[PDB]
Length: 195
Length: 132
Ligand SMILES: *[C@@H]1O[C@H](CO[C@@H]2O[C@@H](C)[C@@H](O)[C@@H](O)[C@@H]2O)[C@@H](O[C@@H]2O[C@H](CO)[C@@H](O)[C@H](O)[C@H]2NC(C)=O)[C@H](O)[C@H]1NC(C)=O
Image (cartoon, rainbow over all chains, first blue to last red; front, side, top):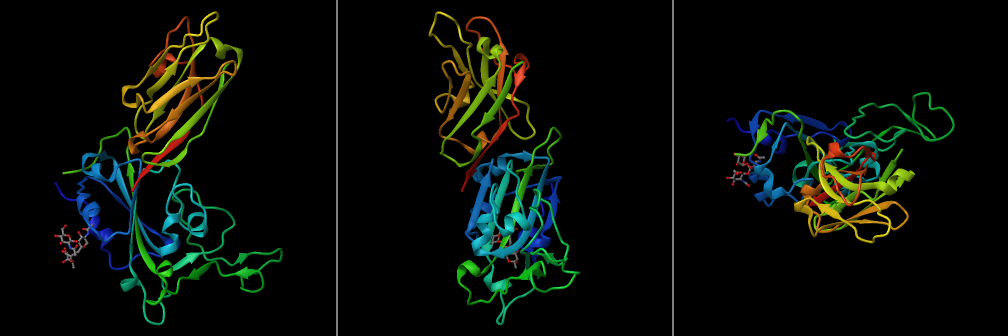
């Protein structure tokens, strides 16, 4: 009977940095996705393996809500088969992804005069993330042939870079809050259905 | 005896098109019906399309289709290459699945339809359909 806590996710005060993205698993609840697809606030609402209109008719074992902040140019990387700093080093979707990617401009919330430097992204990594893998380490990245000894220097970089969100940034460089919904269907009793 | 290798999967927008190929290694393939199955997440393997074996002295070809893909999907078999194709038009989000190629030795123009009625299977190719 109880409704799914989608409000806790979409309307959370603070969102996670993309390198340390947040995940909430949702189960044993009634999901009304109509609040989502009807609203005009989202600038991205692309689904994979499901039609957005029929979401209230489907039943799943679990629904996963991953949320973080990236800049506008990088929302596109939140899709299966994508490549780039975000898709390779921060948040990676699987090829068999079933779910929806939802994003909206958050410049009024996540930028500040002088810059918001709380939102970080990983810029280097020795190898690509696996699907839904998370890397929160902070070791100096060795971009050259010479060891870094744990300190920054020539070809030796701090792995996390700040976004520096200023309200006057071009819309491509403005903060976007992203919620990725993953619909898990198993040979098991469904626990998240529509009304 | 029969090795099946699919290819041609990928991501595509609702309404778009896709063409899957499956090549069969082995002489047993020529006397085998061949077909396509698909498996969505959390579901059993289900029939998509099938095509009859090569029969000497005739050009007649029997096929069979799952009703929900009639007209949108077409199965075809290459002459003397033992490769089958699945032309996939007007794709819907609900077409998302792993698509498997299958082969089954049989007699005459029979096209089997259950997954337990095909012996040989490929590894699968992923098809994902998006919708704005
Ligand atoms: C996220 O919140 C919006 C807006 O929340 C409103 O303001 C808050 C401070 C609080 O007072 C909420 O209770 C308010 O509703 C939600 O959008 C509202 O949704 C309701 C129900 O669909 C609708 O009647 C209102 O008109 C909507 N308001 C606006 C401005 O669109 C939204 O539903 C919340 N998201 C989720 C996933 O729950």
